[PDB]
Image: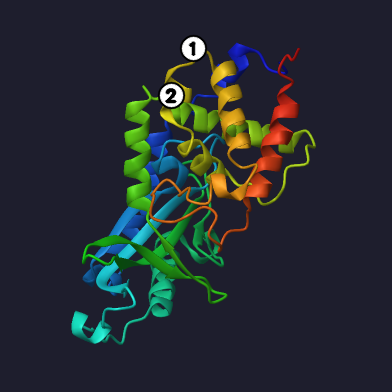
Amino acid sequence: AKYTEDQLTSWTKPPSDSEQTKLENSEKMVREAISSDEKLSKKTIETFGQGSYANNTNVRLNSDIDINVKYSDGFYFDLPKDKSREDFGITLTSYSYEEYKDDVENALVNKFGRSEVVRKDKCITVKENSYRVETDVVPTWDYRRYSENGNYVQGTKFKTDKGIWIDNYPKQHIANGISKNNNTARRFKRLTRLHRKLRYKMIDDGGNVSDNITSFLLECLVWNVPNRIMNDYDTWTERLKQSIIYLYNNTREESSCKEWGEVSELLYLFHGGRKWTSKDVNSYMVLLWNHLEFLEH
């Protein structure tokens, strides 16, 4: 094996002892930028971490914290095709997502200064300093997806500056990750961190990792590793090996994994709209396997 049991074990750990303190300080400073703003303070706006700090799966020291500022005085929605938006109840508003993202930028600029705040395609960044971690603020709106039977699931929706509309379910992602971690004696998030770290390590020493393989994708893949692979093997060498075998075997043909969801279980991994394919995943598993140099016969 290229890495010892001690090395793999150490890469299952958070990269600092104060991950939660960093997340909470970013959340609070953004929440304050919002409540100090005359315009936005009058609206229902919830500030919450999403992303790898909120899921306690970050592995890069002082990497960006992802902070959602979700406005919920109106919600976008989607209905099944045999239901009428009229009969559901339509609300018209002169407010818009575009104005909202500008407003959030203004509030950030007022709290932190124009030089510290950078508008980007999908977020607004607050630059790090000695006291704060670099923070990506994602303004979103409330979102409801209704199913056939009349139930709905609630998430977030936003629009990139290039005009792409994107739905997410950060709360169900967080809750589900916590469930699987509870059912695996906390090995699910340790295995996630280990896989994420191995990816960065292969990239750093020159490996041919496809741009299509992201840290988010790796968490979704480990999510789809059944709990017994975490629970029934006794070392990290073996849990990692078995997880790779499972993911390789089940991406050799697209029919084996076409139903896999992301952690929220409310979006698919391989139903379009993604920059990866299951073939990409399979080839990454081959690369990782060959990189780890497990002893053969």
Q: Which residue is mark 2?
A: 228
Residue drawn at x 50%, y 37% as measured from the top left: 58
Q: Identify residue type, mark 2.
A: Arg
Mark toward the start of the polypeptide (1 vs 2): 2
Mark 2 surroundings: few (<14), some (14-19) or many (≥20) residues within 10 A: few
- Whole-percent x and y of residue 111? 40, 61
The residue at the point 80 percent across, 37 percent down is 206
Residue at the image position 36 percent from the left and 22 percent from the top: 185
Residue 85 to residue 281: above or below: below
Which residue is depicted at the point 46% across and 49% down?
A: 262
Q: Give residue 84's quadrant in the image.
A: bottom left
Q: How is the image coloured?
A: rainbow
Q: State the SS at label 1.
A: loop
Considering only vertical position in the picture, is 37 above or below 64?
Answer: below
Amino acid beneath label 1? Asp
Residue underneath mark 1:
234
Residue nearest the viewer, comparing 83 with 174:
83
> Residue 175, relative to residue 289: is it above or below?
below
Counting from the top left corner in percent of width and height, residue 68 is at: 38, 57
- Vertical order, 232 against 94 (above or below): above
